[PDB]
Image (cartoon, rainbow, N blue to C red; front, side, top):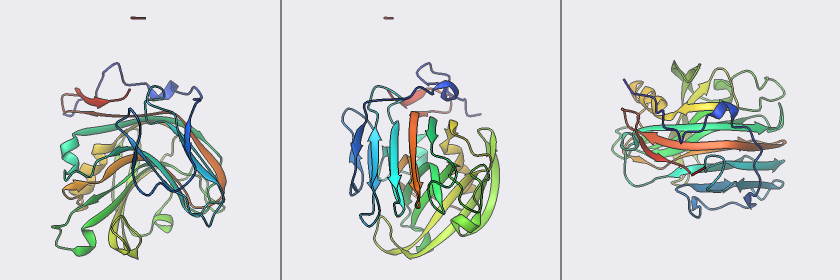
Length: 272
């Protein structure tokens, strides 16, 4: 009933594999969202100065779908680099209609990002009227891929022994089953200081490095399981997170777009 967009501006992710150049790089923690010149997107870096060199380099407004970046880490302590929509304007997810992200990247191999690592979609939402005070702040992940570790192959999806928490259910979208996990973070660092909050994960059962993520489909399935997002979405960004190791992530394509149920474009980036 939701019509997939067929607009020509959408770049086919499967063949979007030309190496990009001319990045603009950020080598320190950004202190939250920082807007990008001539772009609807913002970036954020979390680069612990107790670890080694990390960077995020944005490929600019006019190539690679507009949100493409490369990141590098050298023995970080939980590096996070992310880029995409920054919202935080008191609106629930449904306000943004159907959100999609087409992507294509290369990365370093197995065991180059420490014991845990995440690639995919990430953000937060606030739900102050939730009766359970634990559920008034939400951190969320849609996990397309990871680097595995010494114990587990990067071809094998991570489980609750990496994420923590409880398997709530699953569904199939964009060519794979996704396991849905809820975890409670007890008195942990957050966008609101040290506190208790919840995390929602969809873990792609068949990891991949290119494709399209039907982000809104995850949000709907979470809410059906009682994993509510509330009424103030913070952001919706493409993330690389590396617990440790020495590696890289290098996107040839990250294209966000939003469409209504008829499949008409609401927002997209970017004569013969």
